[PDB]
Image (cartoon, rainbow, N blue to C red; front, side, top):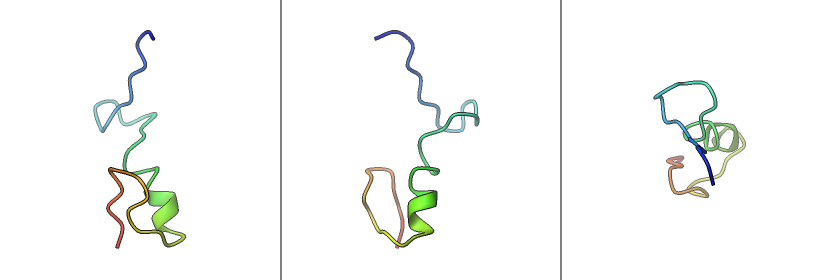
Length: 39
């Protein structure tokens, strides 16, 4: 698939984790995503 690198603070640029939960947690959704730790 090539280098499809999802970074987790490693580059802190195009991150998937803690942003894909962040904007959703802002709305109010709990654990929709594996890495989404929203209450």
